[PDB]
Length: 379
Ligand SMILES: C[C@H]1SC(N)=N[C@](C)(c2cc(NC(=O)c3cnc(OCF)cn3)ccc2F)[C@H]1F
Image 1 (tube, helix red, strand yellow):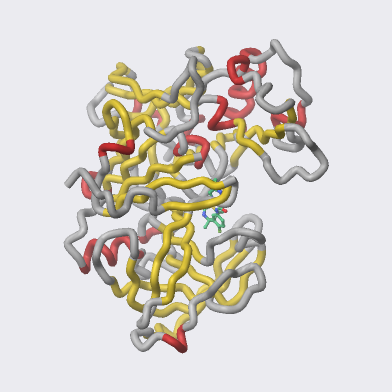
Image 2: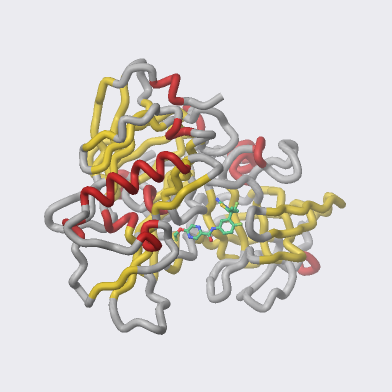
């Protein structure tokens, strides 16, 4: 129940292009690389020869393909996909030894969806039915997986920060992927992986904001987002505090707003000048919280694709949000994250693969006594 050597290192990717798992669709099996995405609920795959695609789902080749005779148009704030809904046989070669009949959205037109130069051709939406397109009757993949097999209602993600990697442990926890203890936060509601942030610290210095701001209008765990995204006010106070803590060196305003990169000579990054960032999360027990702490090496992420610079260039990967807090790859790269769906909870433990230096490490610590944690949730 605690060692899944088969599924260790089943995630690949490129920096800033996300984390993908190999998947097969149809009979005979068609291999596809699929973005692992805890911030959506559709299993959506390229099904037409978009020029950026390495491969695509060819329904005509699958004898087990069934048509639901229903389309879906999915817009985002920037970009879209449109698909045809059907079902087919789906398996995960480096996952559990099973085959599932799952909903597939066959992507027939898209815009700013696929990444030019990326090595994935679809998205595996791991969140719940409530946010599935077009509605909650379109059963997400993981629900079908759990319903149809004896795979436990749990998956865990170790996201390791040009090549990235890690593990998606399907049906369990691999103890070699973390150090110390897992600490669990409740899933507030089963739509996104919603959580409640209870306290925020920059280098141990509390932001002293009304904790309702931290979760305005929600906080989510999202492997499909690069940044730690913060509500506008929280971002402002956080940046003011990060500025103060790092005032040893001055940086342009546009860097903090993600409008410019900032570059240093190779190996000459002042990591120690930048603060740690701590998020206190609601614990399992009344008045009990725990704290997750990330490093500058999580939120100041390298931009390798700069043709106009011979130096080491970085993006400030904490940005403002109007959809609430998004604990993206910036958070998740620090931690082994257990999506304990059976128990409506998310476990955090320090990642065995997280990027750190000789002085500071990412941390998961508790218990702490935090009162009025329920007031932090926005209604
Ligand atoms: C608005 C988005 S947010 C979300 N969770 N999921 C959706 C389906 C979505 C996500 C993405 N992700 C990425 O490209 C990406 C890149 N780098 C990452 O980490 C560092 F490597 C993580 N993810 C691409 C297209 C998408 F459509 C959309 F809903």
